[PDB]
Image (cartoon, rainbow over all chains, first blue to last red; front, side):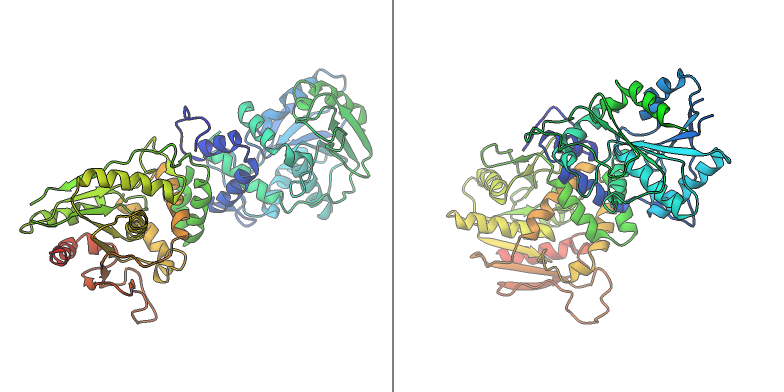
Length: 273
Length: 268
């Protein structure tokens, strides 16, 4: 019936805005996931290329896998990389993008086509150097899956850093806060292209499950809830059984990797090698 | 790219079925008008009174190139038949910029009924629809008759049942392809189409009191392997049932004068 008549758009962005204004992020995410079925997609035979984006320069290569939100891309690491740079003996860093958010890239048809494409960029960028993968929010899901694929094919990273991971199919607090997230990722920045990419990766991440990896895991989790939590406990918190190290980072699900990315850089640094 | 570019990919790949489902879903985020906050509807005059014939009111259909322009071929023929009845078109709210969609069937039809009865100024009228517009002319006849009025007639052209469309199920993709070329569809027309798909999927072919002139296409728009007449529009209990030259679309393009000579004679 109309939450903000002043808005004069009509595409998916306007429909997106009207979803978040009326508390229907879940309904909208499904819409976007169904929409991505009509985006051309690349498969393993004709993989579109992927280029890692340099981020900074005894430690292994650090590789940040971009998230799958509209706000996501290499940019999301730049505070972390900048804080990482001015550290003594700091690792060199790169960034793995998720293809399709930029024009006019295809999304993957399958996870195998994605990880085959990201894995060839990765090994070409790293040479024989050991690497450690990292990712935050949905980028944490994306980095664990790439890990699965690397290890399954006889390779792998030296360790896996997973900042504030949740299960998309079992969202816990991240479902309760879904509309709150959709709010943030817009303002942080969104066209139809980026929005259907988010839809396609959301479809990918409905088949995701919290399965083990060989690589030692570092699990960073925010100190503050991003939304409100009526139960009043820390039941909202990200979890990872069998993590080598679990470490709290000040800030919330997002501000841990902006206003407080300095502390994450320091703890990552003290954990490597 | 947007919903225009997804729509064409769906049609290019034979998936107009999923595209109608998507737009139905996408439309549930369109701002809507209820009966309380009604969006005004205005009739579009097409042909002047040339009696004592009733006013013909075509009901606009629900696809992306529907509206009062779909009655230009028909209304031109009508205006050069001798002693013609006048005619106006009734648009469907939500397809033009800045317009909202109807929240409920009740909201749309109270808006339309208001407008239509204003414009008539006492004159009896005949509701006329083609394709999904037939379902809308029917659904408004039901609404009016339920509330103590109604048209003196109803003209259903090539009406199918959306939930169980038979041949229009088979040909949905040819439908979508043609309605695009006829147009240039934007997000706002695709999302309106979707809103009207949602309401039409609940539509059933209930009987009406007014006499029904049923007009149907001679030719199968798409191919029909069965080789029989199971592709044709079907209205049991119609007053009159006439075949009109052409297929679902050209029956109101090239052969509109055929439809209009026939309507004209049926009315008088």
